[PDB]
Image: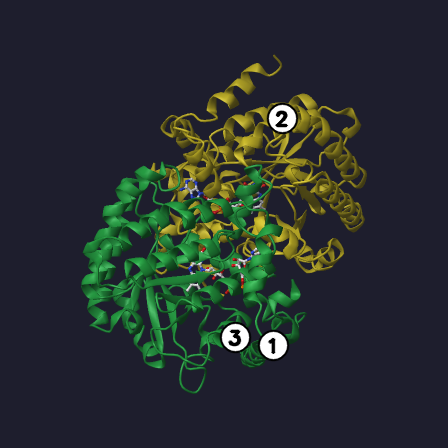
Chain colours: A yellow, B green
Amino acid sequence: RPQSTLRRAITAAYRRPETECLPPLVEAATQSKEIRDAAASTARKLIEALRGKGEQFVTGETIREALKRSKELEEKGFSYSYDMLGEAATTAADAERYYRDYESAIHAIGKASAGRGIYEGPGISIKLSALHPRYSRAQAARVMGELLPRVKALALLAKNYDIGLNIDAEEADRLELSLDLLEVLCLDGDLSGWNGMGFVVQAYGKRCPFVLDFIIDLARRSGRRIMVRLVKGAYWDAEIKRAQLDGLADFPVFTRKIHTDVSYIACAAKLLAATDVVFPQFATHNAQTLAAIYHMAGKDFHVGKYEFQCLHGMGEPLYEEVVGRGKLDRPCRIYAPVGTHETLLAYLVRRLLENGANSSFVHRINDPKVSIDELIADPVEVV
Amino acid sequence: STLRRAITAAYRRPETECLPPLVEAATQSKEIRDAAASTARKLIEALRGKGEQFVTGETIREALKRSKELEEKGFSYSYDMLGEAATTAADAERYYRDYESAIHAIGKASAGRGIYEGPGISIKLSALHPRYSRAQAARVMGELLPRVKALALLAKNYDIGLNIDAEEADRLELSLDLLEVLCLDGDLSGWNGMGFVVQAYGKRCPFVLDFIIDLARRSGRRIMVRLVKGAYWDAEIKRAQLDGLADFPVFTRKIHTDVSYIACAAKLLAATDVVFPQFATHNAQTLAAIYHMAGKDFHVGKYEFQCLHGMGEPLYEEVVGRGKLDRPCRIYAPVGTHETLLAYLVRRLLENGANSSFVHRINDPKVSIDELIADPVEVV
Ligand SMILES: Cc1cc2nc3c(=O)[nH]c(=O)nc-3n(C[C@H](O)[C@H](O)[C@H](O)COP(=O)(O)OP(=O)(O)OC[C@H]3O[C@@H](n4cnc5c(N)ncnc54)[C@H](O)[C@@H]3O)c2cc1C
Ligand SMILES: Cc1cc2nc3c(=O)[nH]c(=O)nc-3n(C[C@H](O)[C@H](O)[C@H](O)COP(=O)(O)OP(=O)(O)OC[C@H]3O[C@@H](n4cnc5c(N)ncnc54)[C@H](O)[C@@H]3O)c2cc1C
């Protein structure tokens, strides 16, 4: 079977015991004392800068409005990825509506990009659940045969304007389908010459390093430089609840928060060693995570090597201390939702759980009981 | 029983079938409609001149100290030690200890004020059993019953209210069976503090109320009944869609929940001899309707309003006190850390951010006062 070894490794990791997943990640995430000392200084600076000085999550109601509101931050060195809000389509008519939303957005974003390309100019992010009715329930063969022509058509428009098109990561049980779709698109000759295809991998998932191995190898055999957004993950609370009801003895996600942090750093090390064939995009609002990757990546940098990413309404204060020659001189792409209350609910719940959780960096930075010492501590050394 | 059969039969009764009996009961006379429109306009005009926000204190001692100001203004309290959906035996044990310690503190603070003038407590059954939603009902009740009875006995000892909050629709039957056992338990005789929430967004609501009113009358317990719309609507919809069902256990149009609430309020106001109705709402039109439906006769203990801490103060400052409507309001007061706050806080966000919610529409420039005072019966 093609890629038998890489695919078997993903499947074997799906619900592997958490204690067995961690040792290789801890080793891969271990950095030198010299690097850890330098990163602690950077993280302290970022946090000292930070601790001083629903509509909040949405950039605009239409793509035209969102694009207009993006000019100020683009002038400062930020880029954008626009998300037409909407997911989990329940009818064919809803899936067709979302498809048309994305199509119209690509034309508008492509015009605004004006030839800036996939790294300096804006792109789009899509959710597969918006494009197939009952995405979570229908057999993969039926989902594939109807979804693939739709995603290909959107990818062709993005190619035509030379903008990025990212497939967002959703629930753990749709990782396999989405990855199979990524493979088919990356091997499709009609998309040749365009490196804008992107894909998210969630470091809270046990399969993350093995999915990355598959994607890096896919980049090598397809000739596409795949954009890879490394995230921790947005669905943790729902995944725990679903696994409990499913009767599982071992879950598809980690259950200790610092294990996700270690997983993220280990996976960043793998991505940073493969920048010839992937474009790593480090999505995080955690200043300690950011500092660790900034130092892991070393002194040599150019635009197009890698970037950081943040969510609209959450990451701007931190990344104002990152973008720009006087700061860390590293770019950041803002994930920019577009829509109204009618399409905001699912995304907003995930933001509430992210912002309100006692374990989240964005909560802890405002917690008087959490010292700066603890905020800059390297989680890898805790394990 | 016949009353319990009506509850089970209504579980997923088609929505269009549920409405005609509610529309009739929620229909008010023109004089009452006109008075309610006048009161509601006055309340809304005062309003339009106006997660730490949702927590009264980290501990029960802190929350009690902060309650003195509003208690002398005419408010009362129901304290909620945050916590729900226990996943382990250790978690359910910890929540039990929190509820137990809260009852001792609240009961000592009550100092003989009784169940209407003095503070009470609210509990969630899902906090007290480690597999509350995922285990067999008869077994869940058989382990939950001694725990809830022990808490009820403490509440009786101090003569305070103890309310069972309502949670997911698939747990209504279990919790109702628990209420019946407690109300027939001779060890709790002479105490009228047992309370129970019924959710008007549920199709079973009027039949649950019939069962509870009859249970109160035959048991001699003046059951405190908190009538709410409901806090879990988005979750019930998502579960019912995944379940492949065509008919859900909740209404799908917000106006139907509003009509259901008014119809159920009418049923409760006709039964104040045997139940203590507690009208929990932040909607000034809903409040004004119930205020006039209740009539001119009032005494402390007949009924009360209720609100959530951090949400209801602007409205109820126009209600409590002799310069206002002279009706009491009990504040639901969450107590706990940010850790235990998360699920409650999310529900507060689905409630406050929803375009259909009164608390959002009150600030929405596109929504007229004329629309806010519309009578749901006349709009459905
Ligand atoms: C631009 C951008 C795009 C994103 N796209 C996606 C996407 O397509 N799909 C997606 O799923 N996520 C996505 N995310 C990630 C998600 O939305 C959160 O923003 C992210 O997980 C928060 O991580 P952090 O490093 O900012 O914060 P931190 O506070 O460091 O980490 C918080 C994270 O830890 C994890 N976590 C919390 N508790 C536990 C626990 N007990 N055990 C194990 N893990 C735990 C969760 O992943 C949580 O979000 C994206 C994030 C950004 C910034
Ligand atoms: C003191 C207090 C205690 C409470 N205790 C509980 C409890 O134990 N259990 C519980 O479940 N709830 C409880 N609630 C209710 C819940 O938390 C909300 O506060 C309440 O439902 C809001 O109703 P309202 O009259 O203030 O607002 P409104 O804006 O008038 O009504 C909003 C409500 O309408 C309903 N709704 C919204 N959209 C739709 C729709 N499309 N179709 C059908 N219905 C819809 C929902 O129930 C929503 O909450 C309590 C409320 C208070 C004030």
Say what amino acid the circle numbered 1 marks: Lys
Quadrant assignment for the C terminus of chain A: top left
Q: Which chain is home to disc 3?
A: B
Residue A45 visible within the image:
no
Direction front: furthest residue: B2
**Disc 1 from disc 2: Cα separation:** 57 Å
Viewer-proximal residue among A311 and A75: A311
Viewer-proximal residue among B290 and A77: B290
Which residue: 39% across, 27% down?
A17
Q: Give percent across and percent down for residue A286.
A: 48, 49
Residue A64 placement: quadrant = bottom right
Task: Give whichever of discs 1 and 3 has the lower sequence position.
Answer: 1
Find numbered disc 2 in the image and state the secondary structure of the residue it sits on: loop
**Disc 1 from disc 3: Cα separation:** 14 Å
Relative vertical location of residue B156 with respect to residue A155 in this rendering, above or below? below
Dot 3 corresponds to which residue? B288
Say what amino acid the circle numbered 3 marks: Ala
Relative vertical location of residue B366 with respect to residue A54 in this rendering, above or below? below
Dot 2 corresponds to which residue? A139
Task: Give the class, few, some or many, for how many residues have Cα within 10 Å of label 2's Cα (few <14, many ≥20).
Answer: few
Viewer-proximal residue among A257 and A44: A257
Task: Give the class, few, some or many, for how many residues have Cα within 10 Å of label 1's Cα (few <14, many ≥20).
Answer: few
Discs 1, 3: same chain: yes
Dot 1 corresponds to which residue? B30
Relative placement, left or right, of A73 versus B40 is: right
Which residue: 48% across, 50% down?
A354
